[PDB]
Length: 91
Length: 89
Length: 90
Image (tube, rainbow over all chains, first blue to last red; front, side, top):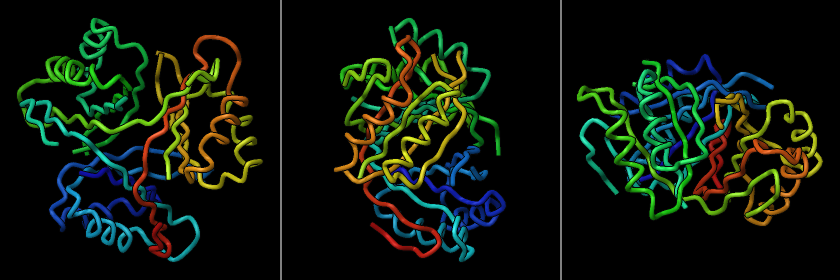
């Protein structure tokens, strides 16, 4: 499992969201961030390793404009995920 | 050392906070997040490996309601922690 | 590559920012966080492994005051970085 964090232009949110739903990406967290100080959105998703590349492509395709400031995607390892409602774990 | 991030229902904050203090969990960071777009809180703590399971349980017990949307906990590795005040590593 | 997250006193931002520019640190993300509930800023940067220690020192030197609440720095692994504009990966 990997965490994928994407720093995108705020107005791209909808587009990106749509794409991620189309790839059956379920859980997803978004927070307001300042980068460059420009306002950006940070999207966080956690997916299986096999999905990573796929997801990246879609985000890229949805978040891209062609100009500097399109932002960036970071992939990092996740050891464990726990669903609070049930306490179910996957590793 | 592991980073523990929990995305919870905002109103659960107090409860969760209490529990974490009861387990001697000291440093803790909280930010507003939108998930699902519902308002959530993201809590971040960094603890020793041996504490991980314990902490998870408490968070679960404190943050749970029984309904969809209770949120999620992610555990990820941390290589290094540095205290800014002293530079201790 | 490593992600460096620093939780600092808000007013230190400028100082810290200057220092990071002086070490050629380019991309950098800042968000408002509540820690301890005191208002803090979380700075996130991703750098090559070889840079890590350097960066840490500068942040420390820039963010420090000597009192409790100076905050903390966490270093964690990053597997992959992708530039959205081009799709370039490292």
